[PDB]
Amino acid sequence: ANIDLHFHSRTSDGALTPTEVIDRAAARAPALLALTDHDCTGGLAEAAAAAARRGIPFLNGVEVSVSWGRHTVHIVGLGIDPAEPALAAGLKSIREGRLERARQMGASLEAAGIAGCFDGAMRWCDNPEMISRTHFARHLVDSGAVKDMRTVFRKYLTPGKPGYVSHQWASLEDAVGWIVGAGGMAVIAHPGRYDMGRTLIERLILDFQAAGGQGIEVASGSHSLDDMHKFALHADRHGLYASSGSDFHAPGEDVGHTEDLPPICRPIWRELEARILRPADAEN
Image 1 (cartoon, rainbow, N blue to C red):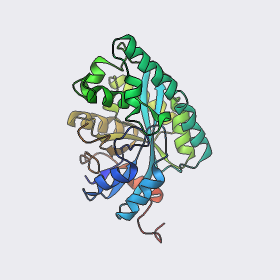
Image 2 (image 1 turned 30 degrees about the horizontal axis):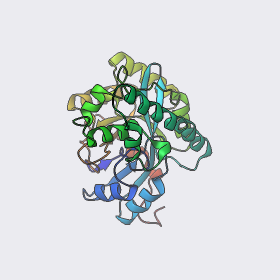
Image 3 (image 1 turned 180 degrees about the vertical axis):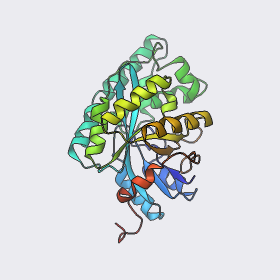
Image 4 (image 1 turned 45 degrees about the horizontal axis):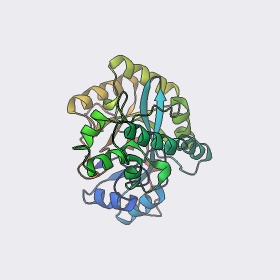
């Protein structure tokens, strides 16, 4: 499929600027794209201009960090108005602790014998307020302390390991509410990544819908075909629309292309057509 509704830019943790990531995706002749940056909308105007220039329909998007019970989940919004005040203030409230968290993550790794990690991570981060674990991981690989990105998180920056600092993000109700209040649709992102059986996934889905959530990512760079299959079933039982995303961050860690949705899925882009920013102006 030529649709990609999940990817990042240097606005938060992607390696490519909004223009660059759009241009990369463009090589694949995509029918639709959505930039969903982590906890910020700052790259949307630039990506929209870049997408328009290449004649590619675009959707304003974002990916919101959520603490649901003991779990961290991600709720993507699609078709949002980034200038809606509640959403903007919402995203800002959850960015607030990132820097202090990152400094502590640096200090934690130092206590564990790896010095210089906050400084090193910051070399990969354009906007300090957006410093994240992905930046730390790029440093650890690049400076040669860790073999690759997968291994970084096996040994570090996750519960029980040096560098991990526990943190509380948005509530599920706030995140879905900000997205829906902004005219968008809320989407449980890359659910295969969560440590959950069918019971937690169902509970998650039920809390999600009660909050106004209409979607879930079925096709994802993070999913195996079995994940695809089973989240399509979860989706159908609860009447959720299916999204698709590459989950692209950087080359090697691809944007503009996803796996065809299982025939049972009701694709979310069909529901978002009125929020799609069309390359032709008269069509907006």
